[PDB]
């Protein structure tokens, strides 16, 4: 019955995933007919869009607009639509992550140094990724995901959430660096491409709009859980908590006419970011020069790195989202989700568009947005395809709705990203055990890993996971940032080999439990 | 045993107050030997000082510096020292209020129009106030305070707290009016007397410093009540919650060198605000011209208004602070506190210094700062004289410590005033019953006025008290602002005559309870 059981039949996992979820397909339309779904669509849209605008911007900077915002928005939309319809876990938000950006920047620098075309280089990586994922899904390689315990899951989940929060603050700090609090400013600053010098009030208003949006979001989260107003209205206001926080703080910025704040910019229409470099279809054999056969074969090694990058990112996100603690009854498919996400990425490369992955924060945020809460415990989860479908479509239609987005500050969305980052820590026993380091040992909750485990041994087990978070944080920073997925895999040996030397069996079963 | 019992002996109340509290005088020194007292001294100092600086500023503006900051600081200090030593309730913070400011502005305009000297006019009001309070304390007029129920007490307490919060926001809004968010500014702005035009970043940083100080204060309030850190450290950090909030946000402003924020300004030394107008001793018979005998006698009617103003302000503040719900075991004296506060005010007028009153928010704030909490319930209150003594001394020594105060923003203190205003609503059944209007009728607490009172009749009783708050708010704004104490007294008839026509006896006993 379990998803991560090795069947024996070639593509046995893929079919057993399709046989499981597609029976509840009519449910996946009708379960979306609630207002909490509509609220989630508006929330996850901005969570989905702004990274595509940002990473797209960076891609445009890093690769001389050979790939950019236009290409990433279109990829995010088409893969998002297809995955929402055909996927095993529609709650996964498919998009572009940092580790994928680090590879594009790395692969561009390679392609430059060796004097071989970059965008056609990615097509061949794409073909290898299609070859690998079919081979992996054929022999049910996603069974190995079962060995990835809560230990590795939470270290990953917690790290990703911390980095999200860090980068959200790094974005705010940057505004203060570009628009410092000076005594005097140049009243003449060209604003066509970007502010050409520091401006008054921009940095502090950015802080106020971020702080304000985060505050309101967290108060309407608290109001939802409170016992104020009629229950019907209390949920309607509460579920539309984030959309309401955005609307009012967007309106607050709109009425402030004189002060400048950075808004969401999108391309004018649907065209490639550099028309002189490429078209909509990338030629394998080459665009200008002859693409060499040495790299056509050698592209396997980059593709094997990209596979490991998408796989762990996506399969650990599928583990976190489809865990027994949450009320996911429809069922998850680790084989069909891997096949589409990695498969589409390969075909996306053929059109010069970026391959994507089930991103951890956006997926958790989207799942957490569709969870109805009782009392505190989770009653059920609104598992349906329409949230993801409509989000993916809106990202597609973001170019058409420029007049709407052009009056939405980034500062506002930075408040929502902070809310996303904080909220993502909720269902993580690592973060729970980190707060127990500060609580005295007579205020710890009545849980399995407190009653029949010694408090100093609990804290040692927590301490070892911090040392793993610390080591993983140093890697992502250093030039060995694409080696972080391999460092995270090394936490499986740590749990399976080393921890049972210092700890006993009973302690590890209670600390690292599959279901609690 | 009760304080508000009419004895029969002339000055029977005054002596029975002295006989009650002075036995516990050695306790009133030794009970101050805790860190929560030191924390309260630092907190209430800024709560005490900044109004004396502000109202002193306004007095300097309203009366051509015939009375100003110097005079008010010295009055606040000398009356504060004397009252801390000799008073019946040392928890009362004696200072200058708005209703007293409205009288000075009103009496100045009179004294101008009729062409009689203002500062000597106040001396004669002062003599009438000494005559009245002695007469009132002789025949134990403070017995009438017993008829002032929770009904009037809470309407007053709630109104004063709302106005405090409103005026705190009015102060912030004014910074945005003087330093608007413009596209362009004049890089040349003389700053000697005050900014001579709008400046960039001042208004938003003011908002950030206010919001920041309020946030930190409310989080260290929450941290105190939480179950984090060792209990010893948890209280030390919690009880120094407001001082810590001020220190860090003062340091945050200190490291920002380029941006301008308004700081606490004090006089250079101890001299009268206008030396050409007056000296340190005001002559009854006159300074320049002959003071007419018509007003020497007619000053009774202004003095009778000032008496009613100080009495209700101070005696209702003594009721609110020394209520049975709180753990005030040392005992309060309504006769001795009235004698000193009004008496000193009369003698203060002879030196050209403003008469004061037991102010509601500062007194409650000071009382709330010295309450130790259990678990949620109040264990005891740190009733001692040293808090009030040291606060009064620090206000006296504020002129000497200009270098310390000159680097404290007002924006920071605006965050503390917001914290004071919110925190003052805690022990008010009116505010509690206001929140029940929004809560559904199956989430109301298990209290006497919910179980055996119909929910629609509770809300009607709450509604009638809002209409009183509304009527009182209109009076404070209109030119009949000195008629507000009389409008508040009319809420006694309302409770004693009108409410028992629409309500039953049992309902009023449960809604308006002396002890709950
Ligand atoms: C735990 C609580 C922590 C607080 C978190 C809050 C984060 C910060 C968010 C602030 C709200 C956003 C304000 C936008 C800035 C306004 C700019 C503007 O144009 O306004 C100009 C206006 C008026 O100025 P004006 O420029 O229009 O005036 C005209 C100008 N002349 C005269 C030149 C023509 O000012 C304001 O609106 C006042 C300031 C903003 C509102 C204050 C918000 C409250 C913040 C205080 C702390 C929190 C309060 C908590 C209370 C409840 C208890 C929980
Ligand atoms: C309930 C949640 C509500 C929280 C909001 C509370 C009210 C708002 C308080 C805001 C904090 C103000 C402190 C910063 C003051 C400005 C600093 C400045 O100007 O210095 C310049 C510095 C920048 O350094 P710099 O200017 O020296 O850089 C050099 C410049 N050049 C390159 C030109 C030479 O500013 C900063 O440090 C960045 C801003 C810090 C902001 C702090 C984070 C607050 C985020 C919003 C609120 C949400 C947080 C919640 C997190 C916890 C979860 C509960
Ligand atoms: C914003 S949007 N800015 C932003 C956000 C992210 S995010 O949301 O993907 O965390 C990043 C990427 C940071 C990151 C790295 S990187 O780029 O520092 O090497 C590595 C990993 N490792 C893994 S798995 C995670 C995140 C940048 C900018
Ligand atoms: C600042 S600090 N300045 C300030 C402070 C206050 S207060 O007293 O709330 O700290 C006020 C409000 C004065 C006030 C009035 S008045 O003068 O505005 O009519 C009336 C009443 N009603 C009664 S009793 C109380 C206070 C203004 C400015
Ligand atoms: C479009 O792509 C081409 C190729 O990178 C860029 O054209 C080159 O620009 C670089 C830097 O100036 C120089 O090598 C030459 O000017 C061009 N030669 C090449 C390699 O084509 C162009 O900069 C790109 N434009 C965008 C939109 O990024
Ligand atoms: C000091 O007090 C005197 C009296 O108010 C002020 O001097 C007068 O100013 C008023 C208003 O302009 C006019 O009557 C004359 O200009 C002055 N004659 C007097 C003595 O009345 C003086 O402005 C005050 N200074 C301060 C510090 O406020
Ligand atoms: C683009 C920026 C300005 C943010 C946009 C957010 C908008 C679309 C959000 C904010 C508040 C939202 C509304 C809040 C509450 C309800 C009641 C519900 O029964 C139907 C939907 C409805 C009527 C929502 C529709 C969408 C809404 C208007
Ligand atoms: C482009 C990428 C994403 C997909 C390429 C197509 C290949 C690899 C996949 C797509 C769906 C797959 C099929 C799905 C279901 C079955 C039924 C099973 O009883 C035998 C295998 C078989 C017939 C699979 C064979 C391989 C298959 C055809
Ligand atoms: C499901 C429905 C609503 C579609 C949603 C996605 C839409 C908005 C997006 C996804 C990808 C987009 C296409 C991408 C590329 C091109 C080629 C260009 O030469 C003309 C526009 C065209 C054809 C775009 C039109 C809009 C498009 C079809
Ligand atoms: C090695 C360092 C630099 C890594 C940084 C993480 C720090 C904060 C971690 C690593 C090891 C951890 C310690 C490991 C073991 C114990 C014993 C326990 O009874 C109390 C907590 C305590 C004392 C931990 C506190 C947190 C700790 C000090
Ligand atoms: C004037 C501005 C900068 C604010 C001044 C606040 C200062 C005086 C406050 C803020 C934090 C305070 C400290 C916080 C904690 C303690 C521990 C206690 O066991 C003794 C007092 C002591 C050491 C306090 C002394 C006073 C203190 C330093
Ligand atoms: C500050 C101003 C008002 C103080 C002066 C007011 C005068 C009238 C007050 C101050 C102290 C008072 C005395 C204090 C104590 C006693 C003892 C008692 O057994 C009889 C009354 C008697 C003798 C009081 C009479 C009134 C009194 C003399
Ligand atoms: C209890 C101790 C610490 C005293 C505290 C209050 C001190 C700081 C204040 C209160 C009133 C003040 C006095 C008020 C008036 C004058 C007259 C002037 O011509 C010289 C200064 C002098 C004499 C002041 C000196 C400082 C002073 C004495
Ligand atoms: C200045 C204005 C606000 C003065 C009027 C005060 C308002 C808030 C008061 C006056 C009478 C009150 C109503 C009296 C009775 C009831 C019935 C109860 O089952 C629900 C609340 C409700 C409907 C009250 C709501 C609040 C109310 C409307």
Image (spheres, coloured by chain):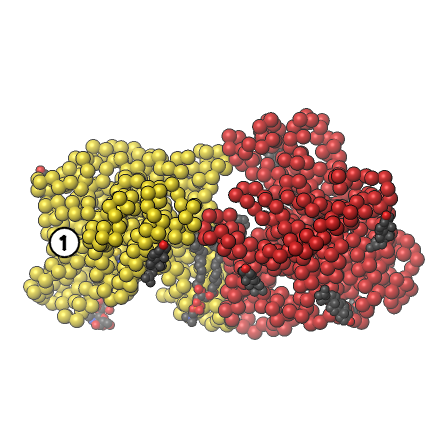
Chain colours: A yellow, B red
Image coordinates for residue A439, horizontal then vertical, percent:
42, 50
Above or below, B177 relative to B460 = below
Image coordinates for residue B422, horizontal then vertical, percent:
58, 48
Location of ligand 13 given as a quarter of the image: bottom right
Question: 10 Å neighbourhood of mark 1: few (<14), some, or many (≥20)?
Answer: many
Res B243 visible: yes
Image coordinates for residue A303, horizontal then vertical, percent:
15, 57
- Please identify the quarter of the rendering in which residue B487 is found: top right
Query: Which one is nearer the viewer's eye here, A274 or A66?
Result: A66
Query: Which one is nearer the viewer's eye here, A362 or A397?
Result: A362
Say if disc 1 is inside 8 Å of ligand 8. Answer: no
User: What's the residue at 19%, 38% (across, down)?
Assistant: A2
Above or below, A327 relative to A392 = above
On what subunit does the disc labeled 1 rest?
A
Which residue is situated farthest in the right direction here?
A: B293
Quadrant location of the C terminus of chain B? top right
On screen, residue B513 versus residue A388, left or right, reads right
On screen, residue B194 versus residue B234, left or right, reads right
Quadrant location of the N terminus of chain B? top right
Query: Which one is nearer the viewer's eye here, A51 or A423?
Result: A423
Element assignment for label 1: helix
User: What's the residue at 40%, 61% (across, down)?
Assistant: A172
Which residue is situated farthest in the left direction here?
A: A293
Above or below, A105 relative to A439 = below
User: What's the residue at 38%, 41% (across, down)?
Assistant: A446
Q: Which residue in the structure is indicated by mark 1? A: A129
Image coordinates for residue A24, horizontal then vertical, percent:
23, 33
Res A159 visible: no
Query: Which one is nearer the viewer's eye here, B313 or A291?
Result: B313
On screen, residue B145 versus residue A3, left or right, reads right
């Amino acid at each position: 019955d379990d998803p991560l059981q090795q069947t024996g039949q070639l593509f046995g996992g893929l079919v057993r995933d399709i046989r499981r979820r597609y029976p509840y397909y009519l449910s996946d339309i009708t379960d979306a007919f609630s207002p909490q779904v509509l609220a989630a669509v508006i929330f996850i849209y901005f969570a989905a869009l702004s990274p595509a605008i940002t990473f797209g911007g960076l891609l445009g900077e890093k690769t001389r607009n050979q790939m950019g915002v236009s290409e990433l928005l279109i990829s995010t939309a088409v893969q998002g639509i297809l995955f929402a319809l055909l996927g095993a876990q529609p709650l996964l938000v498919v998009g572009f992550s940092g580790p994928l950006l680090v590879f594009e920047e790395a692969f561009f620098s390679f392609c430059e140094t060796n004097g071989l075309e970059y965008i056609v280089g990615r097509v061949w990586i794409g073909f290898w990724l299609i070859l690998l994922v079919v081979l992996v899904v054929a022999f049910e390689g996603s069974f190995l995901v079962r060995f990835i315990s809560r230990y590795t899951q939470e270290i990953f989940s917690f790290l990703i959430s911390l980095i999200f929060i860090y980068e959200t603050f790094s974005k705010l700090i940057k505004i203060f660096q570009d628009h410092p609090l000076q005594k005097t400013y140049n009243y003449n600053v060209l604003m066509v491409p970007k502010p050409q010098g520091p401006l008054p009030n921009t940095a502090l208003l950015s802080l106020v709009l971020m702080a304000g949006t985060f505050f309101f979001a967290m108060m309407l989260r608290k109001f939802k859980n409170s016992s104020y107003f009629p229950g019907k209205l209390r949920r309607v206001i509460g579920d539309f908590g984030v959309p309401i926080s955005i609307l009012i703080m967007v309106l607050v910025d709109f009425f402030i006419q004189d002060t400048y704040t950075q808004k969401l910019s999108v391309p004018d229409g649907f065209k490639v970011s550099n028309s002189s470099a490429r078209g909509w279809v990338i030629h394998p054999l080459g665009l200008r020069s002859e693409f060499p056969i040495w790299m056509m074969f050698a592209s396997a090694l980059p593709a094997l790195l990209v596979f490991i990058l998408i796989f762990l990112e996506s399969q650990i996100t599928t583990l976190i989202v489809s865990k027994p603690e949450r009320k996911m009854v429809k069922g998850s498919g680790f084989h069909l989700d891997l096949l589409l996400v990695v498969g589409m990425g390969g075909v996306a490369a053929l059109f010069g568009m970026p391959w994507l992955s089930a991103t951890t924060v956006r997926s958790v945020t989207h799942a957490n947005a569709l969870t109805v809460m009782g009392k505190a415990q989770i009653q059920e989860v609104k598992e349906q395809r329409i949230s993801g479908l409509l989000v993916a479509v809106l990202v597609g239609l973001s170019i058409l709705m420029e007049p709407i987005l052009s009056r939405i500050p980034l500062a506002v969305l930075f408040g929502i990203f902070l809310y996303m980052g904080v909220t993502s820590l909720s269902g993580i026993q690592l973060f729970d055990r980190i707060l127990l380091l500060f609580k005295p040992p007579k205020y710890h909750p009545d849980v399995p890993y407190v009653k029949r485990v010694k408090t100093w041994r609990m804290h040692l087990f927590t301490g070892i996971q911090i040392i793993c978070l610390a080591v993983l944080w140093v890697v992502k920073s250093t030039p060995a940032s694409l080696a972080l997925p391999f460092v995270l895999i090394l936490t499986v040996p740590l749990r399976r080999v080393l921890l049972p030397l210092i700890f006993r069996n009973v302690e590890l079963q209670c600390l690292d439990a599959d279901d609690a």
